[PDB]
Amino acid sequence: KVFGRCELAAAMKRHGLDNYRGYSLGNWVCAAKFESNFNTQATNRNTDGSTDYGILQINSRWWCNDGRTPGSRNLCNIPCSALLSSDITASVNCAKKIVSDGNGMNAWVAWRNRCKGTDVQAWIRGCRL
Ligand SMILES: [N]
Ligand SMILES: [N]
Ligand SMILES: [Pt+2]
Ligand SMILES: [Pt+2]
Ligand SMILES: [Pt+2]
Image (cartoon, rainbow, N blue to C red; front, side, top):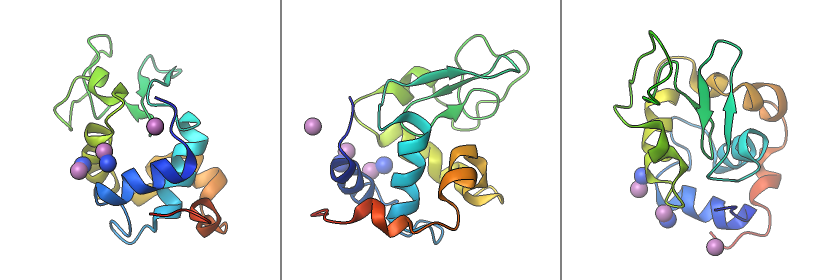
């Protein structure tokens, strides 16, 4: 599923991401835009052989099992394919564990490089949430 901007903001609000560990909804919408272009199906292979999955590009190195990432962990205890559903529940639940692990949203390279310290409120402008 390719979400619209306000459609995803509404879904992320429903699943408890608004102000989750102090990160406004605009931060999460910004992160999703630059990680996946709002596409639940997005996959990208990393240089270390791990792959990033779904709307928030959750990495097999630490968070999910994709059956082809040697010596990695599965800290969200999910198959990485669960992260590609039109339903964002698995991605949200796993993102809450990630953002809570001490590094906050710095885990998301696209957030650090394109969202951090910008006017993220612009990402929810006009949205009926
Ligand atoms: N949702
Ligand atoms: N969720
Ligand atoms: Pt839709
Ligand atoms: Pt939902
Ligand atoms: Pt939920």
